[PDB]
Amino acid sequence: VAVADESLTAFNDLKLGKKYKFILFGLNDAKTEIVVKETSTDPSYDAFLEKLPENDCLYAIYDFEYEINGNEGKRSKIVFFTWSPDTAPVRSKMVYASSKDALRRALNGVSTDVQGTDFSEVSYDSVLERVSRGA
């Protein structure tokens, strides 16, 4: 499949202008291109978690900002998620496993990747632990 130019524009605006806090990508009904499905400027991580579908897959980009120790400000890292819940259809899980690289090879500046199979692998403390260390 191909990456819709709009998906690349939405990424450049998050990356270079912090225009969005997170973006959700998915396949078009035709299942031929990867488009944006939802964008948001909500800083609450909970708000992002609430949009993750329990029975379907998606891809997402999150602008993860965390406190950098030493009485120094913050750091921000772009995290790429593959949301693929055990409760999702096998054909969906697979088509999304397939199309992942199309969208992933195209994004430049992603610091860390997360493969969410459930809400524990995508929890705040869990993302923060991966992002903090040698990511």
Image: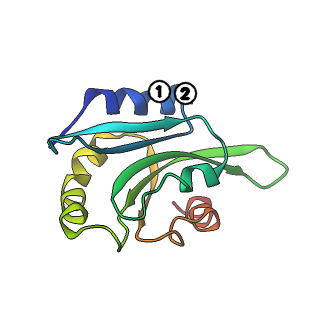
Q: Which mark is residue 19?
A: 2
Q: Position of residue 101 (x, y in %)?
A: 24, 52
Q: Are marks 2 and 1 in contact (CB under 8 Å)?
A: yes
Marks 2 and 1, how far apart at CA: 5 Å
Q: Nearer the viewer, residue 53 or 62?
A: 53
Q: Which mark is residue 13?
A: 1
Q: Position of residue 15 (x, y in %)?
A: 49, 33
Q: Is residue 23 above or below residue 130?
A: above
Q: Please give the name of the residue rendered at 26% of the width and 53% of the height, measured from the top-left corner.
A: 100
Q: Nearer the viewer, residue 37 or 103?
A: 37
Q: SS at mark 1?
A: helix
Q: Nearer the viewer, residue 37 or 79?
A: 37
Locate the N terminus and report the quarter of the image it occupies.
top left
Q: How many marks?
A: 2
Question: Taking 113 as reference, is 71 left or right?
Answer: right
Q: Please give the name of the residue rendered at 36% of the width and 51% of the height, measured from the top-left corner.
A: 59
Q: Please give the name of the residue rendered at 48% of the width and 35% of the height, measured from the top-left corner.
A: 39
Q: Is residue 29 above or below residue 91?
A: above
Amino acid type, mark 2: Lys
Q: Please give the name of the residue rendered at 47% of the width and 26% of the height, measured from the top-left corner.
A: 13
Q: Residues within 10 Å of mark 1 (few under 14, many from 20)?
A: few
Q: Nearer the viewer, residue 48 or 122?
A: 48
